[PDB]
Image (tube, rainbow, N blue to C red; front, top):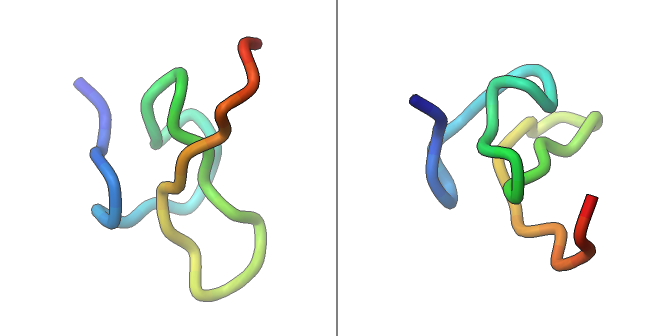
Length: 36
């Protein structure tokens, strides 16, 4: 399972495949939009 929008995380893996975690505090799971 992964974290949803505004769920919290530290790394990109922590967030879903589509959701990307910002590498700058505050660290949260956001939406990328671009297909990996």
